[PDB]
Amino acid sequence: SSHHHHHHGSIDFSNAPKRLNNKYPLSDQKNEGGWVLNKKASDEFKGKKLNEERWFPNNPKWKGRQPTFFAKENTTFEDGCCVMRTYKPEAGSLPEGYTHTAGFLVSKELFLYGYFEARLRPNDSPWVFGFWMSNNERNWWTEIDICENCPGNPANRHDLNSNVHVFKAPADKGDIKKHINFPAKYYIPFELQKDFHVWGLDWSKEYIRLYIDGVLYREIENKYWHQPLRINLNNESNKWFGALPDDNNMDSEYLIDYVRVWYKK
Ligand SMILES: [Ca+2]
């Protein structure tokens, strides 16, 4: 697989949609899609505390990819953002194989189709930042990686990654016995970590459509992704991105301004 090197194309932002309102998707500000805001699941992240009726404060099903262990204390709320930090606790404090901590939130709600959007300021540190959706339930396990990137590794500053996975699917839902995925990366003309950007997903029975700052950059025929999914926000380690801890570069912040969810009227 060539996706460590291959930019399929570049993404042009000269005609990118202007922000007109905070009521509809950035890629559809005039609401041609007939969207309705999901007020249960959407979060503007105001205040100083997690809404723990809406979110789990860590990941109950995954401790983390070594060497980074998900912890509740790494996620705080400041100036209208969820803020995720990375720490190195004292030696011996974490379970075997783990040396650093990162934050993780999982939605208590499950979703099937709709528009999903998050405004994100990446951490400038060698941890992947993630806004993605997944579910592992009754031997059906699928995942949509709206945003899985690590510009905090300077070699990756101009990459925009995307992927979708089927880890397993029963006979009547795709019949997948071996993990399959479909990664694709694109060139972006700015360094991803410098500013907030808006990731969008228009997920329908027919297509997965992915948007960056309102610009469509990938379309996927929706063959397999018909399973309800939870929303995940987190930092993690991943050797593939060169996303391994750096004790001299771990003081950055992953900022989530909002998560917005819409359904069809
Ligand atoms: Ca906010």
Image (tube, grey):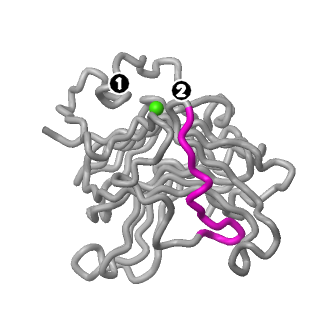
From the viewer's perspective, is residue 177 above or below residue 89?
below
From the viewer's perspective, is residue 144 above or below residue 27?
below
- Label 1, secondary structure: give it: loop
Q: Nearer the viewer, residue 86 or 138?
A: 86
Horizontal placement of 240 versus 181: left or right?
right
Q: Give how far apart the Cα atoms at labels 2 and 1 are.
A: 23 Å
**Residue to which mark 2 is pinned:** 12
**Residue to which mark 1 is pinned:** 22
Residue 93 location, quadrant: bottom right
Q: Position of residue 112 (x, y in %)?
A: 25, 56
* Marks 2 & 1, CB-CB < 8 Å contact: no
Crowd band around label 2 with a 10 angstrom C-alpha radius: few (<14), some (14–19), many (20+): few
Residue 69 location, quadrant: bottom right
Name the residue type under label 2.
Answer: Asp
70 inside magenta stretch = yes
Horizontal placement of 173 versus 107: left or right?
left
Q: Nearer the viewer, residue 190 or 186?
A: 190
Name the residue type under label 1.
Answer: Asn
> Which residue appears farthest toward the left when viewing the image?
265
Q: Which residues are magenta?
A: 64-78
- Is residue 168 visible to us here? yes
